Length: 89
RNA sequence: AGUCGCUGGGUAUAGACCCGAAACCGGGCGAUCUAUCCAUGAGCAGGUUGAAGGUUAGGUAACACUGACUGGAGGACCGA
Ligand SMILES: [Mg+2]
Ligand SMILES: [Mg+2]
Ligand SMILES: [Mg+2]
Image 1 (spheres, rainbow, N blue to C red):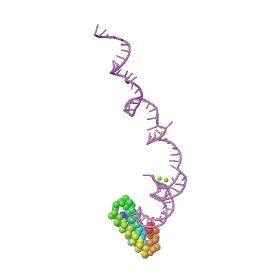
Image 2 (cartoon, rainbow, N blue to C red):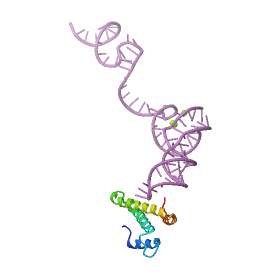
Image 3 (cartoon, rainbow, N blue to C red):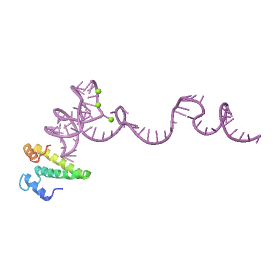
Image 4 (cartoon, helix red, strand yellow):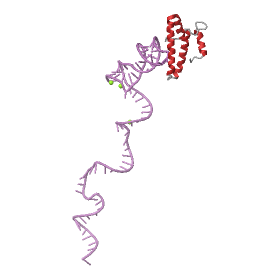
């Protein structure tokens, strides 16, 4: 929950599939990706924060699970999501 | 019966019959050899090996990590 409400409100509308959409995998993956990348700065300065890293790993596993489900449903939608977000490194 | 000479034998102090040390001390001369240093120059054919690093393709949540290409380290190797 390191993302502010403004940042959350910022990225939800760029990845929403329709008005009022906050549960679609694109919003979820984009929500996790922005939080994952933001936390990278914290873990650089705080390298002994093993307890907060457990939460970061969970966000990484959650994003992987969502992308794998999006793989089965619509591969074209999956492809656009990672290209826009720059995943699959 | 001493005393002063002269000559000779002996003695004392002197190198004291001649030659001969290892050494000791004083003043000088030497670092064109050599030992270390200082400054300023010069030399080291040829052939190997293949560190760190880099790039790239992967890979990682990120750091990592892997391959290839590269790179050219070393009181390193063979050898004038
Ligand atoms: Mg000389
Ligand atoms: Mg040598
Ligand atoms: Mg030799």
